[PDB]
Amino acid sequence: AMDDEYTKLLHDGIQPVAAIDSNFASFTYTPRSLPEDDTSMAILSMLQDMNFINNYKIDCPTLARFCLMVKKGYRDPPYHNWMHAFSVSHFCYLLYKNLELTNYLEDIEIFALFISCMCHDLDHRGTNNSFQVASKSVLAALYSSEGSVMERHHFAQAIAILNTHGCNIFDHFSRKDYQRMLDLMRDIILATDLAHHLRIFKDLQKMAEVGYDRNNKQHHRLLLCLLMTSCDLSDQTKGWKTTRKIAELIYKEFFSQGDLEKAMGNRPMEMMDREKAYIPELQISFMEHIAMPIYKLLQDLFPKAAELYERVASNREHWTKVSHKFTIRGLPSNNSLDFL
Amino acid sequence: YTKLLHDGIQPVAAIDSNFASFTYTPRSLPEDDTSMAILSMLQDMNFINNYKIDCPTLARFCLMVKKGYRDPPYHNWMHAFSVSHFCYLLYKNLELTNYLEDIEIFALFISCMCHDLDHRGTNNSFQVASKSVLAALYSSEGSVMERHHFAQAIAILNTHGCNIFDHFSRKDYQRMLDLMRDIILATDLAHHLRIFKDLQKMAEVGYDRNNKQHHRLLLCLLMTSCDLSDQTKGWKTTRKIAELIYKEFFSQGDLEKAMGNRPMEMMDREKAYIPELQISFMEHIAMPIYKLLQDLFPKAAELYERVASNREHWTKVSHKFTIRGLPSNNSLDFL
Amino acid sequence: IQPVAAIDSNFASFTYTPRSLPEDDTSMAILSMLQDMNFINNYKIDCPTLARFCLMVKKGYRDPPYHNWMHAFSVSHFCYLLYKNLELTNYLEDIEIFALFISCMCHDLDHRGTNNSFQVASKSVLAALYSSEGSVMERHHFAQAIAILNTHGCNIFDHFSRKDYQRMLDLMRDIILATDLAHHLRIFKDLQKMAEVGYDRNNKQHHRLLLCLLMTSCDLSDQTKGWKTTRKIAELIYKEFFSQGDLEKAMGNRPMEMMDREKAYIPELQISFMEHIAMPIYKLLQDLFPKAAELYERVASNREHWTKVSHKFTIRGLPSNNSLDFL
Amino acid sequence: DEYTKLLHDGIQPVAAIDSNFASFTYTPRSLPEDDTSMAILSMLQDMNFINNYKIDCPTLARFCLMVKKGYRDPPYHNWMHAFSVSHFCYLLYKNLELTNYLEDIEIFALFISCMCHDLDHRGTNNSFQVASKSVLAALYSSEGSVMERHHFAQAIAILNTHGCNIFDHFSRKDYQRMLDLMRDIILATDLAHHLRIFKDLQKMAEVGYDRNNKQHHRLLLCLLMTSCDLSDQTKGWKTTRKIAELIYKEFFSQGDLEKAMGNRPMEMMDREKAYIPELQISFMEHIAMPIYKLLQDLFPKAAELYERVASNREHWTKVSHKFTIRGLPSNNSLDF
Ligand SMILES: CCC(C)(C)c1nn(CCO)c2c1N=C(c1ccc(-n3ccnc3C)cc1)CNC2=O
Ligand SMILES: CCC(C)(C)c1nn(CCO)c2c1N=C(c1ccc(-n3ccnc3C)cc1)CNC2=O
Ligand SMILES: CCC(C)(C)c1nn(CCO)c2c1N=C(c1ccc(-n3ccnc3C)cc1)CNC2=O
Ligand SMILES: CCC(C)(C)c1nn(CCO)c2c1N=C(c1ccc(-n3ccnc3C)cc1)CNC2=O
Ligand SMILES: [Mg+2]
Ligand SMILES: [Mg+2]
Ligand SMILES: [Mg+2]
Ligand SMILES: [Mg+2]
Ligand SMILES: [Zn+2]
Ligand SMILES: [Zn+2]
Ligand SMILES: [Zn+2]
Ligand SMILES: [Zn+2]
């Protein structure tokens, strides 16, 4: 089945990006609307449109195999699946199309960001770093001493794909350019650990305050981290219907984890405990404390990113507005108090 | 045989427009058309062309497999056929090629055909209690009947003119045998119960397409899903199968009593309360299997819902096992 | 059924060589041994049934150089010698000794002159049926034995109590499985421990382990006779091994050195077998049974003889034809 | 195939491999590579680990072949290194009577760690990983022992491969203990680690090993692992000379790569600067002899090992002069 997919990807030609959807390159576009079966071709279309295939003389058979392998490397938990990776990668493309990234970052850096987006949650098992440590998982055996357990795994999985015969999209690169690409993928993927973001937050604030300096290599590193985080959280920048659906997915995933924690006798965090978690309040707190400040930083650095912050702000207000619906007024639709 | 050869392999649609739907009841097919249906399904999955299987050999194999079933009330050829049909349904309705190798799915279907060969309508404990030759040969390794079924399959493949795999490469031939052994052994309910927590673990972490143990576990789950598939149809199927199953069980119990042994409650026709037994089997054995299948394949949700609906039907007809008033003949002679 | 003394006055001695008995007289010798151990009378074994059983077992051996009926017969005879000289009734239940003897008769049924790994590498039906459980040939031998018992007129145990019938089956299975050399090597440390602490007749696990060790000592008993026996058996064994190697070569495989007639150096291989496998077994037997010391002595003396004739495998002077036309 | 025979034949009695197999004088690199997997099984059987840990024989056979397959083929850090190190572990077990000092599970962990301790080595050292910014250094960024963290990770991947879990018999508690023991022991193979603990090892040797002291167990495991890793120095002249050839080939290859990259190699890795006999004598005096003296201090029965290493050191001094060309080269030519 992967064989036949590959055959079509390679021999059919790369679909023009404009044939995917008329609004494909707009911040309003919702990539989750694309059928999953169309997504590997859409990755090829974006890579083509950003000129990466020609600029880096990426081998077409290799690229087709790599894209399919990355897709195959995602499991199917409610949120951390290939459609999340696809939507994150699409947002990277949007930033490229809409924010003039070539004025801030090196070509190889923008390339690294996009490839990292595709790979950044590889082999996610629907549980977080704390769970790896508490459950004494294999991944914690490997990586707990360094921290960012899952992110180290995702990076390791990306390298394992590249090291698979026929999949190394970078193997004609110079030793220096190869080393650079793999180092950028390390830094960017590790940047997806929200703990890392929180650590560097004041440094990001300082960068926005002083103004971005293109000749400052630390500015490049910080900006990459900020863009990766903005891609990861980008579902919050769409319409109400997207944020609502993404809340159902992420809390389903969390509460499944909470259920497993209880099953091993540990008290889950409130936010993972389906008996305690109050979703509107958790999502509001997340938006206020994490998401809004990110997109405000992005707006500070890229004036044309203002619409993103405004959508997150509006979505947070929507959560305040529907919160009252989490209180049962009258009787249930049942007409029954049996639930008591 | 002559009729299969004469007709050629029939397109699936010519059998029934609904043949590849979960709503379809394969037990409705006349027994004399089932071999044709096996070939049709294999053709529709393209296993014949893809593995370059010799067609007369396949016909001979299918008929020999069919012949290898006895005629107890439940564990007969129509059971093996309906189990094999469900495997085909899972191929057609779930994206099994997304999760399993082609050889894995082919071995699953062939295992379905063979998985109860020479069943005598008694269970493993009975073989041991009765000191059958089967127990003498297999009891120390466990899964007595399942080791026999696989041995019967090996005997069929090694019958002149029946070896559908005799042109496979050495590695693929060995692959088939290992797969069939594992899948057939997985049909022992005791085995399912032993691995249930590992199936749960797999559903919890999510199926890993690159984990060979997940492949093995998924094949076990699919096999058990096929074996119990009579529960995923409508009421009339679950009702009829209950009749057939309990007929078999009660005949076992009668034999155990004649041996001086106390049969299990569900095999003792003076103690077995069918509605309660059937409801517990459905709630605590079948539903958990179809819930696992659903967790792994969203599109399998209707199967779990159907088992739940049938379970509800049984709860609602339970009261009919209590004789209110007089029997229909107006007689108390039955006392 | 003929008395044992009528067969040969030395019949019950460790010095007796049962391979000296004509093959046409071996079935009667089986019945005579069973009668002498009083098993027929004690278990009320039906004689015509026993006779039919014995002939079917004999018929169930093929004719490779080593793993044939005469092997099974010589193994069974050593079991009898153990009974007679070591007073086994002091150590095991009657049923266990009976099972041991019947197991000896059956333990290589339908052997093809090839080992377990050969069955697996050649993808024989036997490998298909048994490779996942291990001890491929031994599972076959046991299955062949079950098939014989279940042939009309051949079930020597069919009047036994269920407890005794089940015990017989379980013992036969366990003893036949113990004849896999891989099994012996795996349990060797447990046999050593039993020998060191001392055999406890009230310990059922000691009963089990001792049954394994006696079976193994029956299986290798050709090493406990004189020179002519160990010499002849080496010939038969290496014929089998080299034919297996030849088949492996024709399959595009590389045989182990010992089965490669172009590499095998027989005296080296024979001496290693005797020193590292056979001698340790007979040494343990001596630890448990001081009356078995002569057996260990014979194996050790035979090993010495092999060392003494090793030089003959190097061509000194000229070949008998006075030609170097082999170079 | 090879697997078929490994599984379906018996495990060969250890004494049948070679009459001198269990002696400190035995050179395990003399065993053909094709026989080493079976020798591994023979050793595990003789140490009774197959018994005490109820190890499924198919599982053990697959594990042994998977570990062998996990070694690449640089001059020194290959499977035959792992084999010789494992064989030395067995020699210590047999000659030093380790069951009187360590718990069974500790000795088991030591042996498996010997097998696995250089998995996937490419003939480059920890310095190389950092300087070159490899994936390994990218993962294991916080402390050193980059390669050792990776060797452990490879061992874990093997144990987690369907059909290779030789630890399946352990309780979850003992499984965790085993994993943590393997990490500790494999990390002890970083010579930097040995150098850090050297003073504590001397203290332990001076006061004497206490089996009731948990720290003593940890320290003994480290010293035993190091003693296995350097065991090529405890054989004859021929072995120390051949191992020198292999390790120095590996060092110089790394150096050539470093030069090409724009990094200056350590002198010992620069084929234009390195003087092997000085380098080797320094290693023998300052690293190897002190390890075997510690072993001898803890275990009188280990005295011959230190004596051999000391003697091998003196042999290097004797032949050192041969590295300055006196007379004409072999070919009678000054064309060089
Ligand atoms: C950024 C972290 C990852 C990726 C898990 C994440 N993605 N997304 C999707 C973005 O489109 C969400 C995520 N995390 C959430 C989250 C985190 C923390 C807390 N938290 C903890 C203590 N206190 C609070 C409020 C609450 C809720 C849940 N909601 C989300 O929307
Ligand atoms: C005959 C065995 C297999 C599982 C194949 C089987 N098929 N079918 C046909 C299903 O379409 C049935 C089967 N097994 C039954 C069964 C099993 C377990 C238990 N059991 C034990 C402890 N606890 C419970 C509830 C009870 C009843 C009986 N009823 C059935 O419907
Ligand atoms: C054929 C198997 C049994 C053990 C029954 C057997 N009988 N006999 C007849 C004895 O009277 C022999 C047997 N086995 C032999 C044998 C076994 C192992 C190994 N081996 C492997 C690794 N290392 C060694 C030493 C070598 C040689 C071959 N020689 C024999 O004499
Ligand atoms: C354990 C460390 C590894 C694997 C690198 C190693 N093994 N082996 C094989 C042991 O049997 C050797 C190793 N290292 C060597 C070495 C190290 C340091 C120095 N050196 C220079 C100035 N000062 C010192 C201490 C010289 C030489 C080279 N010679 C070796 O024998
Ligand atoms: Mg992530
Ligand atoms: Mg069955
Ligand atoms: Mg045998
Ligand atoms: Mg190392
Ligand atoms: Zn993400
Ligand atoms: Zn069935
Ligand atoms: Zn034999
Ligand atoms: Zn090493």
Image (cartoon, coloured by chain):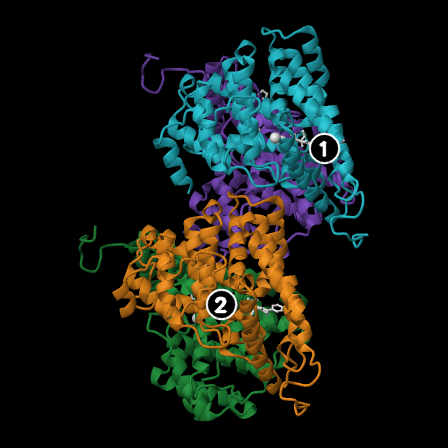
Chain colours: A cyan, B orange, C green, D purple
Residue C62 sits above or below residue A71 on the image: below
Residue B184 sits above or below residue A211 on the image: below
Mark 1 packing: few (<14 Cα in 10 Å), some, or many (20+)? many
Residue B132 sits above or below residue C137 on the image: below
Look at discs 2 and 1 and give the one toward the viewer: 2
Using the rendered view, name the quadrant where residue A239 is placed.
top right
Using the rendered view, name the quadrant where residue D9 is placed.
bottom left
User: In which chain is the residue bearing label 1?
Assistant: D
Mark 2 packing: few (<14 Cα in 10 Å), some, or many (20+)? many
Nearest the viewer among B38 and B110 is B38
The location of residue B224, given as percent across then percent down, is: 54, 60
The reply to whether the C-beta atoms of the residues labelled 2 and 1 are less than 8 Å apart is no
Residue C110 sits above or below residue B103 on the image: below
The location of residue C71, given as percent across then percent down, is: 40, 74
Which residue position holds label 2?
B147
Nearest the viewer among C42 and B261 is B261
Ligand 5, seen in the image, is in the quarter at top right
On residue D201, the disc is 1
User: In which chain is the residue bearing label 2?
Assistant: B
Is residue D138 in view? yes
Image side of residue C268 versus residue D108, left or right: left
The location of residue B287, given as percent across then percent down, is: 62, 59
Using the rendered view, name the quadrant where residue A237 is placed.
top right
Residue at left offset 56%, top offset 81%: B251
Q: CA distance from mark 2 to mark 1?
A: 57 Å
Tell me the amino acid under the disc marked 1.
Answer: Leu
